[PDB]
RNA sequence: ACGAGACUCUGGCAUGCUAACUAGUUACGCGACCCCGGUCGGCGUAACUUCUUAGAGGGACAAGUGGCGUUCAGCCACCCGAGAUUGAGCAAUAACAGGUCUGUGAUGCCCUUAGAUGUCCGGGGCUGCACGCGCGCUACACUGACUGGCUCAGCGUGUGCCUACCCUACGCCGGCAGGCGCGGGUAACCCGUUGAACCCCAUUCGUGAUGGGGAUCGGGGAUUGCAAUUAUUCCCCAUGAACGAGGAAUUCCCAGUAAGUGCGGGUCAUAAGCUUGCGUUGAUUAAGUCCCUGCCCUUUGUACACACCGCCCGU
């Protein structure tokens, strides 16, 4: 029964950026919730990073909504 | 041209039911196959008319609970559609097959009845009717996703998505499988 | 930082455990085994007492530990069925003494771990394996083979340094055993 | 225990009156499919139809009354 | 940009209070006693500072301009009906107070009522409700 | 013979009947915009009741089929079918020491009647708080909060006798609460096609007593009234408490139902956290039982009959 009060970073440090750029385009389902859970960052910060990766073109859009968005990796072939 | 009742973008055919005891109670195949999980009504009027309802419609109707969500059918429908999106993009498997195999795997097949006076603890082992199997299975899936998506950063479109696949493979990391097999354990403990 | 007490992940059948109760449910009740890393357990309503009860919290007492016996376990799935009715009155003092030795060993090793600054799950399991589980497997007693080993090693440094864990960490553990276990 | 009873599935033939303290149980007349000659009575919870096949964890007990 | 900038000030020491830098600038300045959500948008609209940045990366000149808007809001064309303290009984001026003038002026008003012996002052001295509501069924945390 | 039933009102349909410039539809002309064709709740007038209004008649009766039943009363499932159990109204003999003398110029008796228990004026009180109890409202959040845009109803009511106090389109001023000259309706004509809320879409927020929650409290400005202080009410900026899904116990309900959500009426000079109606979205479970709390009939028992909340024995 450990509490472990989360203290999410408001912006990226050095290790989070390349950890994201090497592991997030190698995952099956990408949503800001699972990005905030795995990378211990804020929800809006994950949304901004995912918008940057969408503008870069390494993530394809699946469906957009005001509640949550759905993202997936590129085909490895 | 109505070649196939595509459930938005998923095909209602080529889905396999593994249990024969739930064959006539789950209607998804070739007759009760709709484009939406929202129909008109007059489905809970007589005794067994709810067995003819589509299973995704029953899941959508049982999705809404706890006061502030009653009547919001559109919101539960779009949760169901987004959950089907993560289910299709997550395993590579057709999302209607995942719904069917989870309900079979999460159905409690034996029950204990409270017997005696008020306060005494006596249980008698009975078996569960196949309609009530589907009914408590849908209720268990809905309450597992509901208590997963509470005071958490993870959305309900993802909390519902992880809850069925853990019930589909029988990994027992889901909450429906947890109450299913403790109920089977209680029914087995005193027969 | 926390882990299991003994080397076994899940206990065997017909074994006594001391468990912390958490909440009361309809079919059973949710508890937490403090010596098995707070895993989920179940106590039955009819198994709480052999006679007629008047209220649920006559024997619930949420927050205070109790003694139970494992009736049926499932190692592959992680389910333990507990029993309250099948306990002897003479077992309580021995269970309390065993939990006292286990908790003072866990507190001493936690103190040595935060002195040595080794904060990792696998590294902490390695420290337990090199500190207590080795002498537990050597003396063939799950709990009774450890406290006697620290009691001997408080006076015998040659018996203390038999495990090849480290040098400075071994000195810190010997200092903790000398200061605490007197 | 130490014995895995194989699960047998049985289909009803006739529904009887509803038993139980609150009338929540029901007496049914089920029949086996590996040999269609045997008919026993079981206690079921929930609504049942005619021709509704049920799963049985055990196939050895007999139905008791409301008590 | 999204990478943390250099000299990213975490804890902001402004007006002898503690201010977090991880919160939005339209909401991190609301932790100061006396200023709230509505008046915060006007201040960052008079100053040429966007609302899309956190409070932890702003620097001395912009936070100094915001502190000038705090202390003297009248001649930066903030409307007179937007203020919390208007038409004073001591001197008759329109001003915005930031926790020090606010706390000491509320204390001075309460001792003014207690000295003038109005029933509002007597109810504040006794520790009861002043706006004229029922006390029979509520207020059970008054005294033991 | 009464009661139940029978009877009435409302909902559910009828492209058949009667009818509509205080309701529209379809065609025709004119006008406006665009690329030859679309939109107009823009303007005007040749048929019509498909929408609407409301009158008369019709339609569902266990009527048919297959079973169960003494094959008698009736029950079950199915087909054709808008419905094969819609909801309300009225509601018998007998009595309650049930409530109302504060509904009445309905009322017996008693008290009082000029230093009045009649009446009137002015002020206060019915709101006063160690505490306990009941009906309710808002929330404890991410099935969410804020901000923009999109978009859909039905019951109603409205210038009153002494009695003065109505509902409101439109123009300007002001952040807003609000203010002035202007027009309609004594009402299917005017508010009004009642651009309602919940929902839908798109940003901001990210598990933090937090942008949740708005209690408490300070300052200022308008409206009603002869008069607001013990803030009538409304508006603006600050103040941001408890509350992390609630112990023993207990209430209501089974189909357009519970629940969420808003709109009318009653009180009303100023006026809804209450109540009565209305509409939108819209489920989980069950077609059974007498175990609990009670009710109806028959038999039996009784030392009860102001009737078990009864009666009664002894220190």
Image (spheres, coloured by chain):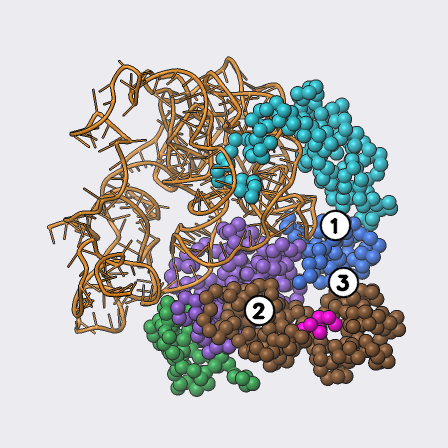
Chain colours: A blue, B purple, C brown, D green, E cyan, F orange
Quick one: A30 or C29, which is closer to the camera? C29
What is the x, y in percent for residue F180? 52, 14
Residue at 66% over, 20% down = E89
Distance (Cα) linking label 3 and label 2: 32 Å
Query: The residue tagged with tag 1: helix, strand or loop?
Result: helix
* Same-chain check, marks 3 and 1: yes
Residue tagged by mark 3? A26
Residue at 77% over, 56% down = A58
The chain holding disc 1 is A
Q: Quadrant of residue C135?
A: bottom right
The answer to whether residue C111 is magenta is no
Magenta-drawn segment: C99-105
Residue tagged by mark 1? A45
Q: Main secondary structure of the magenta part?
A: helix
Around disc 1, counting alpha carbons within 10 Å, would you say few (fewer than 14), some (14 to 19), or many (20 or more)? some
Foreground label between 2 and 1 = 2
């Amino acid at each position: 029964k450990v509490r472990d009060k989360l203290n999410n970073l408001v912006l990226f440090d050095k290790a989070t950026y390349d950890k994201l750029c090497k592991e997030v385009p190698n995952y099956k389902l990408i949503t800001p919730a699972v990005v905030s859970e795995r990378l211990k960052i804020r929800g809006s910060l994950a949304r901004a990073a995912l918008q940057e990766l969408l503008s870069k073109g390494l993530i394809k859009l699946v469906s957009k909504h005001r509640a949550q968005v759905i993202y997936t990796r590129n085909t490895k072939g | 041209t109505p070649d196939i009742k595509l459930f938005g973008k998923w095909s209602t055919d080529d889905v396999q039911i593994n249990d024969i005891s739930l064959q006539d109670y789950i209607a998804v195949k070739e007759k009760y196959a709709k484009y939406l999980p929202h129909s008109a009504g007059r489905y809970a009027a007589k005794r067994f008319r709810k067995a003819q309802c589509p299973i995704v419609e029953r899941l959508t109707n049982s999705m809404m609970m706890h006061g502030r969500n009653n009547g919001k059918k559109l919101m539960t429908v779009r949760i169901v559609k987004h959950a089907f999106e993560i289910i299709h993009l997550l395993t590579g498997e057709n999302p209607l097959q995942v719904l069917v195999n989870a309900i079979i795997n999460s159905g409690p097949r034996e029950d204990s009845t409270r017997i005696g006076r008020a306060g005494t603890v006596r249980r008698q082992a009975v078996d569960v009717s196949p309609l009530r199997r589907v009914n408590q299975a849908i209720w268990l899936l809905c309450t597992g996703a509901r208590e997963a998506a509470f005071r958490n950063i993870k959305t309900i479109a993802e909390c519902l998505a992880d809850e069925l696949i853990n019930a589909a493979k029988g990994s027992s990391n889901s909450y429906a499988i947890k109450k299913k097999d403790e109920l089977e354990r209680v029914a087995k403990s005193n027969r | 930082l926390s882990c299991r007490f003994y080397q076994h992940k899940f206990p065997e059948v017909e074994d006594v455990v001391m468990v912390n109760v958490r909440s009361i449910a309809e079919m059973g009740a949710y508890v937490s085994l403090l010596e098995y890393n707070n895993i989920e357990g179940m106590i039955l309503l009819s198994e709480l007492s052999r006679r007629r009860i008047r209220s649920i919290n006559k024997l619930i007492r949420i927050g205070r530990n109790e003694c139970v016996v494992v009736i049926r376990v499932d190692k592959e799935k992680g389910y333990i069925d507990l029993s309250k009715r099948r306990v002897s009155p003479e077992e309580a003092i021995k269970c309390e003494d065993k939990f006292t030795k286990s908790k003072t060993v866990y507190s001493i090793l936690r103190h040595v771990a935060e002195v040595l600054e080794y904060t990792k799950d696998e590294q902490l399991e390695s420290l337990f394996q090199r500190t207590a589980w080795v002498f537990d497997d050597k003396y063939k007693r799950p709990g009774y083979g450890a406290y006697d080993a620290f009691k001997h090693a408080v006076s015998d440094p040659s018996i203390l340094d038999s495990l090849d864990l480290n040098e400075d960490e071994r000195e810190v553990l010997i200092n903790n055993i000398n200061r605490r276990l007197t | 225990t130490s014995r895995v009873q194989p699960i047998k599935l049985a289909r009803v033939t006739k529904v009887l009156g509803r038993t139980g303290s609150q009338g929540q149980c029901t007496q049914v007349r089920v029949e086996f499919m590996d040999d269609t000659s045997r008919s026993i009575i079981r206690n079921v919870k929930g609504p049942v139809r005619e021709g509704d096949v049920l799963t049985l964890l055990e196939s050895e007990r007999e139905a008791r009354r409301l008590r | 940009s999204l990478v943390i900038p250099e000299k990213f000030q975490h804890i902001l020491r402004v007006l002898n209070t503690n201010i977090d830098g991880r919160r939005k600038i339209a909401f991190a300045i609301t932790a100061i006693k006396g200023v709230g959500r509505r008046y915060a948008h006007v201040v960052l609209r008079k100053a040429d500072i966007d609302l899309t940045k956190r409070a932890g990366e702003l620097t001395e000149d912009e936070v100094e301009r915001v502190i000038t808007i705090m202390q003297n809001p009248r001649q930066y064309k903030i409307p007179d009906w937007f203020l919390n303290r208007q038409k004073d009984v001591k001197d008759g001026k329109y001003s915005q107070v930031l926790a020090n003038g606010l706390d000491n002026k509320l204390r001075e008003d309460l001792e003014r009522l207690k000295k003038i012996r109005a029933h509002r002052g007597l109810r504040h001295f006794w520790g009861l409700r002043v706006r004229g509501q029922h006390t029979k069924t509520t207020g059970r945390r008054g005294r033991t």
